[PDB]
């Protein structure tokens, strides 16, 4: 019950995972969709590399911090390429 | 396809 | 199973098919001569919806399909005041 | 739409003998086009027409097909639809796809009607087809009687009933699967019911197994056909018992 | 002690000889015998240390155990798995199965039982030939091997070795006075196993040793089964042997040509057409002694065609493939008699081929003929009904009409198969009770999918009446799963496992239509599970009461209208309101709940535990029973 | 509009007809040969129902007519332990 | 349809639909009390068929839904109530509409059955959330949104 926005430079894929699941599940998701196998693609959490083994529960993606109404952002980098994800457009000010 | 599922009993 | 919603900026917003079909015009864009029934890209190009609004719309898709059958005081959808009056048109166009 | 369906009418009516296949081609294209156009006009259907005497584009296109490709072609489409069905009854094999598509177009154009979606199909085709098949099978029953005795006649009627049951699935809507067969019972097994009832005696007196089976299958559908067979079988069994347990 | 023995077993499995010597050091004779010969349960295997050491091939471990400590040669325990869970096998049997010449040699030199018989009389020679080590087979042979000792199914080492692709071991057995005329439990000989294997060298060595070909107990000569398996090389060997006469060889040619057009692995219409040339020419080469094939009535599944009696008709299909496949199926049924199990897979695969390209009209009738053959052969056919449900859901999803007589026939076969499975599990054995119950539940689920499809399609009144009668037969039969679920309970349960291929795209459970139809067919509304939950208890726990409010509302309406006690208590004394997780279902039931003084008085009687035996009518005696 | 349900003791139990028609064999008893077109007493004489249990039956009539469109925590109907197993039968006979 | 286009308003602002879905509507006791019982599912469906103002607002701000959810016989006549609710939802009644007291029809239900029927006949409708965020933040929506969206925001 953890919802993620795995963010490429401009591609922002919306995925779901279990709180007690490892990184490799969403890595396989990215491999199956973006067609980049995990041996060549690395993900990031708020400018910090993630390893293949540790689970999402202690990775920082708690169910109280990555609710579906506001998912957590996971970086990406395909080959090294640093986290240079372009942000969204600036909303217009209140009129 | 339906032809793939037939390998079980055969 | 994973359609690609493209915003006006160029922000591809890949979301699951069942999430995206909760809207009317995304079901209509993926109907008729827009199907492309080979599960290759399923790419819709929203030439008018900005990225900061389409992201909130996709998050609404996820939030709705998670909380559609709860009806047990579901958490509020956080819509910024700047996004509102700009998400309203994108919710009218993307019906429901 | 009304200037495009008229174009299809000018391109279809001009076909003197192939208006059925032209109608089927244009109807397939126009039905899928109406579906995809209702998909395209979703904002106008959900925010203008629904909010307001107006008709949604998916419903409007079929309505503009009913009023401009079926109503002017009402006396011409059916006049050869029944002809192709009769030619099928004579032994020929018409294009089942074209005939079934044209027949289903009548029930498909008013699929958006709330109360009676099949009212159009019933009033335009099902009733004329029922009259035509009643006349045709009355003629068939009159033809079979003068050239075949009851033993062959019942088998011929059962074969014709099986062929009409099979043929009804190929062309007509499922709702008329019963009437078309029932109306072709009450022309060849019930118009000559008394004829069968004038001969059941023999069928049971010699215990003709094939004839008894055919006659039971035939008279079961008729409301007042079976009781005479029941009573006469009882009479036969009573006479057999008397002749068996009195010597 | 148990820890020392377990550590010794683990070290013997791992081959740690130094650790084994350390653990076995300073041990008495009783301790030595206990540490070597104790059955330990590890990895799903109940085995002794010597058994797991021989299986692992550790020569040094087994020689240390048999030389320094002299472990007994009576090491019996469960070894291996996957159809080889035979218990009581000695260490020699495991060593022969493990395919290590050194271990079996050491065990034989230490006095292992060469002709040891297990609970299924599994000789070490059979395991050695199954592994394929010729040296182990020989070393067993000179140490007083008994080739008569075989499996309880009369499966000798020669037969199982000929089944596998190993010519050396079967040749060595044949030159060691084998039994080429062996007959198995089903009457099949090793010639049949060699023919279905496709290795002509084994058959050549067998016929060099007086193979003495003969039909099996079923009645399939090895040339015929070689023809059916598209083994052209095996077929073209008995002509050189010159003992198949003329009718047997020509029917072999016909069956070979028929089989190449239907077998998925060897699908080649060119080979079919070539061997049909051979069949036609060998039938029509003499004239005076011309051999003729019989004529069967045409089968509606394959259209209307009875082989091609005129050869010009056969060459008239060189430009087509569909009629060629139909002719192959017709010839296959003509030869095999449409009674062997081998006649169902070809027609099923042809139906699948017609199904992958949306030619459902031929697929449905082909699969219906295959299902009729399976049912008349008294064979399990739950998978065929499952694939019927799958194809029906596929053609429903593509907005294409389903033939009502087709689904009626499928429903007839489904209820007959459910009756067969019910009487099978009525008197089933413990070794197969779990799989029998699984098949019974699969048949129930596929019946539910078929009923859901029948509700999905639109048919006339006569077809609907036929379908309703077919459902009502099973409803009166009252089927129950392993949890006590009737048909209604599964039709209202969201936990009913719907198949993932195509049924899940259409058949969604719970479905309002299937439950309404079951109630119209007379389903027992007040049934129970093993824990007493009725249909209402099952439906009120539904997980999606908002998005699927129509389904839940209609299920509750139908259940209450057909008569359901809205306060019936299960074994935990919970009313359906007490079992309802969602408030939507609670208030729907409360709208459908009618207050009654009988229920209140029955609840008071149950709460106060008043003795109601013979003090009240039997109807009330059960009314307070479930209140 | 006021029937008179006699008990086996002899106690008249005049109750409003709307209340007494919620039964099965009281709506059925006042239908046919006994209809009381003169509507003078509407006796529904019970020679089997005791008085102490017919009183609770009438109380149930009133309680059910009152607490029918409630669906929100209806108060319990106090069936005494001794009168139960005599009121179960008296509710089965009258069809609740 | 002619009378609906005539726009009838009671002194309390109740339109034809409001009186059709109200159990408080007076009924003559001579013989109309034996047949004409309000609210009626058939009457409401017939009105909605002939282009009735589904989201009509009285002087107090209530609509047809705000009146039907207050129905106080939600079991014995439940079906009728149920039908009327779905009829309004089948006519595009806005289930999030707020009256002059800013009370949604859930807040005016005063009944478990009507509240549950309304909740099951209610979609998530991101338009409702966006309009609620616009109204709560008091953003000006004049000439910056579609014409229909101005009335849509005016609902909340």
Image (cartoon, coloured by chain):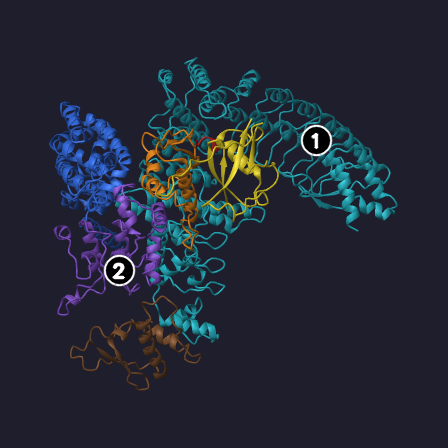
Chain colours: A yellow, B red, C orange, D blue, E cyan, F brown, G purple
Q: Which residue is mark 2?
A: G67
Q: Are marks 2 and 1 on the same chain?
A: no
Assign the C terminus of chain E to one quadrant of the image. Answer: bottom left
> In the image, is residue E350 above or below residue D110?
above
Can see residue E524?
A: no
**Residue E53 in the image: x percent, y percent?**
76, 37
Judge the density around disc 1: few (<14), some (14-19), many (≥20) Cα neighbours within 10 Å. Answer: many
- Chain under disc 1: E
Q: Nearer the viewer, residue E146 or D166?
A: D166
Q: Nearer the viewer, residue E206 or D84?
A: D84
Residue E618 figure quarter = bottom left
Q: Nearer the viewer, residue E98 or D165?
A: E98
Alpha carbon separation for disc pair 2 and 1: 87 Å
> In the image, is residue E142 above or below residue D216?
above
Q: Is residue D102 rendered to the left or right of residue A75?
A: left
> In the image, is residue D93 above or below residue G90?
above
**Residue E32 in the image: x percent, y percent?**
84, 45
Can see residue C8?
A: yes
Q: Is residue E140 rendered to the left or right of residue G69?
A: right
At x 51%, y 35%, the residue is: A29
- Chain under disc 2: G
* Image disc number at residue E589: none
Q: Is residue E465 rendered to the left or right of residue E111?
A: left
**Residue E569 in the image: x percent, y percent?**
45, 64
**Residue D189 in the image: x percent, y percent?**
17, 42
Residue E308 figure quarter = top left
* Image disc number at residue E128: 1
């Amino acid at each position: 019950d953890v919802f993620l926005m795995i963010r490429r430079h401009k591609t922002t894929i919306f995925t779901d995972a279990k709180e007690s699941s490892t990184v490799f599940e969403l890595k396989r998701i990215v491999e199956g969709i973006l067609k980049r196998p995990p041996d060549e693609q690395r993900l990031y959490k708020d400018d910090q590399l993630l390893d293949d083994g540790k689970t999402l529960g202690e990775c920082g993606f708690t169910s109280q911090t990555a609710r579906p109404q506001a998912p957590a952002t996971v970086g990406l980098a395909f080959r090294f390429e640093a986290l240079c994800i372009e942000p969204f457009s600036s909303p217009p000010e209140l009129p | 396809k339906f032809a793939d599922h037939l390998h079980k009993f055969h | 199973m994973y359609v690609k919603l493209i915003s006006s900026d160029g922000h591809e917003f890949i979301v699951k098919r069942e999430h995206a079909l909760t809207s009317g015009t995304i079901k209509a864009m993926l109907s008729g001569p827009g199907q492309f029934a080979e599960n290759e890209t399923n790419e819709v190009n929203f030439r008018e919806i900005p990225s900061h609004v389409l992201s909130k719309v996709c998050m609404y898709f996820t939030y709705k399909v998670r909380y559609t059958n709860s009806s047990t005081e579901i958490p509020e959808f956080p819509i910024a005041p700047e996004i509102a009056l700009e998400l309203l048109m994108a919710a009218n166009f993307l019906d429901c | 739409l009304e200037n495009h369906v008229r174009h299809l009418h000018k391109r279809v009516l001009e076909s003197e003998e192939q208006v059925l296949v032209m109608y089927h081609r244009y109807w397939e294209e126009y039905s899928k086009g109406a579906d995809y156009m209702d998909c395209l006009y979703r904002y106008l259907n959900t925010q203008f027409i629904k909010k307001n005497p107006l008709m949604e584009i998916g419903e409007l296109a079929l309505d503009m097909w009913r009023k401009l490709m079926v109503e002017p072609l009402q006396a011409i489409l059916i006049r050869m639809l029944l002809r192709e069905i009769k030619n099928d009854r004579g032994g020929e094999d018409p294009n089942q796809k074209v005939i079934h598509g044209v027949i289903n177009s009548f029930v498909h154009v008013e699929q958006y009607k709330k109360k009676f979606p099949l009212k159009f199909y019933q009033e335009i085709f099902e009733s004329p087809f029922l009259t035509e098949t009643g006349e045709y099978y009355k003629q068939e029953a009159s033809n079979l009687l003068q050239e075949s005795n009851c033993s062959q006649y019942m088998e011929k009627v059962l074969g014709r009933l099986k062929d009409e049951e099979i043929r009804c699935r190929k062309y007509l809507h499922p709702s008329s699967y019963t009437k078309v067969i029932h109306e072709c019972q009450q022309r060849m097994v019930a118009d000559h019911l008394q004829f069968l009832h004038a001969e059941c005696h023999n069928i049971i007196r010699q215990e003709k197994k094939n004839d008894m089976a055919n006659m039971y299958v035939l008279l079961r559908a008729v409301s007042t056909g079976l009781p005479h067979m029941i009573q006469e079988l009882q009479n036969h069994i009573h006479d057999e018992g008397l002749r068996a347990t009195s010597n | 002690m148990e820890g020392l023995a377990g550590y010794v077993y683990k070290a013997a499995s791992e081959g740690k000889v130094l650790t084994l010597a350390a653990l076995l050091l300073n041990r008495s004779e009783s301790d030595i015998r206990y540490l070597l010969g104790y059955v330990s349960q590890q990895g799903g295997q109940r085995s002794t240390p010597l058994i797991i050491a021989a299986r692992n091939g550790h020569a040094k471990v087994v020689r240390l155990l048999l030389e320094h400590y002299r472990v007994q040669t009576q090491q019996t325990g469960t070894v291996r798995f996957d159809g080889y869970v035979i218990d009581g096998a000695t260490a020699l049997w495991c060593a022969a199965g493990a395919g290590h010449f050194e271990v079996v040699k050491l065990l034989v030199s230490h006095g292992a039982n060469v002709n040891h018989t297990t609970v299924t009389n599994s000789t070490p020679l059979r395991a050695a030939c199954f592994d394929g080590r010729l040296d182990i087979v020989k070393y067993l042979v000179e140490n007083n091997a008994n080739i008569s000792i075989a499996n309880k199914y009369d499966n000798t080492c020669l037969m199982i070795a000929a089944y596998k692709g190993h010519t050396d071991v079967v040749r060595y057995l044949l030159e060691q006075r084998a039994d080429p005329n062996a007959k198995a439990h089903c009457g099949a000989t090793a010639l049949h196993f060699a023919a279905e294997a496709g290795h002509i060298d084994i058959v050549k060595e067998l016929i060099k040793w007086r193979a003495a070909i003969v039909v099996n107990g079923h009645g399939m000569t090895p040339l015929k089964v070689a023809a059916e398996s598209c083994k052209a090389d095996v077929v073209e060997l008995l002509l050189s042997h010159a003992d198949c006469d003329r009718r047997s060889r020509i029917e072999a040619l016909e069956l070979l040509g028929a089989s190449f057009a239907n077998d998925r692995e060897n699908y080649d219409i060119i080979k079919t057409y070539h061997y049909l040339y051979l069949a036609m020419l060998e039938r029509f080469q003499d004239g005076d002694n011309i051999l003729e094939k019989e004529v069967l009535p045409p089968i509606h599944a394959y259209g209307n065609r009875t082989e091609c009696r005129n050869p010009q008709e056969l060459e008239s299909i060189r430009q087509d493939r569909d009629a060629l496949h139909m002719e192959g199926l017709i010839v296959r049924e003509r030869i095999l008699g449409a009674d062997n199990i081998d006649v169902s897979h070809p027609i099923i695969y042809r139906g699948a081929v017609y199904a992958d390209n949306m030619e459902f009209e031929q697929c449905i009738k082909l699969w219906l003929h295959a299902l009729h053959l399976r049912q008349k052969g008294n064979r399990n056919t739950h998978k065929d009904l499952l694939r019927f449900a799958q194809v029906f859901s596929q053609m429903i999803h593509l907005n294409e009409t389903v033939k009502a007589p087709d689904i009626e026939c499928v429903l007839r076969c489904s209820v007959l198969e459910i009756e067969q499975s019910m009487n099978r599990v009525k008197n089933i054995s413990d070794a197969d009770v779990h799989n029998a119950m699984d098949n019974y539940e699969c048949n129930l689920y596929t019946f539910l999918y078929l009923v859901c499809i029948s509700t999905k399609t639109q048919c006339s009144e006569e077809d609907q009446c036929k379908i309703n009668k077919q459902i009502y037969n099973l409803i009166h039969l009252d089927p129950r799963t392993r949890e006590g679920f009737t048909l209604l309970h599964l039709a209202v349960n969201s936990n009913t496992p719907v198949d993932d291929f195509h049924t899940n795209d259409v058949c969604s459970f719970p479905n309002a239509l299937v439950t309404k139809l079951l109630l119209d067919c007379g389903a027992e509304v007040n049934a129970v599970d093993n824990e007493g939950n009725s249909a209402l208890h099952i439906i009120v726990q539904y997980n999606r009461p908002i998005s699927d409010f129509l389904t839940l509302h209609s299920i509750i309406i139908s259940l209450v209208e057909a008569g359901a006690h809205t306060d019936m208590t299960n074994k935990q004394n919970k009313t359906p309101l007490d079992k309802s997780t969602t408030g939507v279902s609670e208030i729907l039931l409360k709208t459908q709940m009618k207050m009654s003084l009988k229920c209140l008085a029955a609840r008071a009687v149950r709460a106060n535990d008043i003795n109601y035996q013979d003090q009240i009518p039997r109807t009330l005696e059960e009314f307070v029973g479930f209140h």
